[PDB]
Image (cartoon, coloured by chain):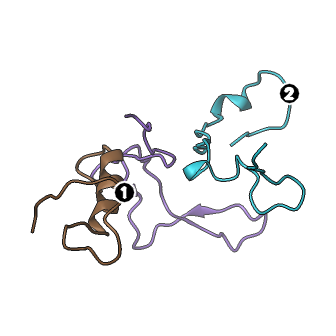
Chain colours: A purple, B brown, C cyan
């Protein structure tokens, strides 16, 4: 007697860290100077962020 | 979260679990043609 | 989830997902309820002597 299987929802497995394929990015300033073209943040904010 | 998915007998068994049967339950009638039995 | 209403194969349609149809059991009534006309004005059973 085989009523099949109840699997309407999908079930997933994930890496321990929550995320892996993460790039490295640097914070940037709004650059009050016009053209609205941002510039790098040389203040206390590390240029490497995952 | 059945460790065991059989589904069927399971539900049936739950149904069995909620109801009853014995012999001195003779309130009213036993049922038609007869024999006298146990579980006294 | 049908990503795009556009017909035929497409790059966007590659991501479509699926989901099984809901179960549907069909069989006769318990105790064959209703197979015989009972307590109906029109179709009434008769058991008479000849």
Chain of the residue where label 1 is placed in the rendered structure: B
Is label 1 in contact with label 2 (beta carbons under 8 Å)?
Answer: no
Q: Quadrant of residue B20?
A: bottom left
User: Badge 2: how crowded within 10 Å, few (<14), some, or many (20+)?
Assistant: few
Position of the C terminus of chain B by quadrant: bottom left
Q: How far from the left and from the top, in percent, is residue C40? A: 82, 60
Q: Which residue in the structure is indicated by mark 1?
A: B32
Identify the secondary structure beneath mark 1: loop
Residue at left offset 59%, top offset 40%:
C19
Residue found farthest to the bottom: B27
**Where B28 sits versus C40, above or below?**
below
Residue found farthest to the top: C9
In this rendered view, identify the residue nearer to me: A42 or C3: C3
User: Badge 1: how crowded within 10 Å, few (<14), some, or many (20+)?
Assistant: few
Chain of the residue where label 2 is placed in the rendered structure: C
Q: Which residue in the structure is indicated by mark 2?
A: C7
Q: How far from the left and from the top, in percent, is residue C10? A: 76, 24
Q: CA distance from mark 1 to mark 2?
A: 68 Å
Identify the secondary structure beneath mark 2: loop
In this rendered view, identify the residue nearer to me: A13 or C23: C23
Residue at left offset 49%, top offset 49%:
A9
In this rendered view, identify the residue nearer to me: A2 or C39: C39
In this rendered view, identify the residue nearer to me: B24 or B17: B24
């Amino acid at each position: 007697e085989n009523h099949g299987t109840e699997d309407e929802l999908p079930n997933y497995c994930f890496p321990l860290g929550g995320v892996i394929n993460t790039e490295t990015l640097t914070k940037v300033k709004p650059k009050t100077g016009q053209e609205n073209g941002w510039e790098k943040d040389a203040t206390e904010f590390s240029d490497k962020n995952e | 979260k059945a460790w065991n998915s059989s589904t069927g007998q399971m539900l049936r068994d739950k149904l069995k679990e909620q109801n009853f049967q014995q012999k001195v339950v003779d309130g009213l009638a036993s049922g038609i043609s007869g024999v006298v039995d146990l579980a006294n | 989830y049908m990503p795009t209403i556009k017909e035929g194969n497409s790059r966007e349609l590659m991501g479509q997902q699926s989901m099984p149809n809901r179960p549907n059991y069909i069989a006769f009534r318990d105790n064959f309820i209703g197979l015989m006309y009972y307590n109906s004005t029109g179709n009434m059973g008769v058991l008479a002597g000849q």
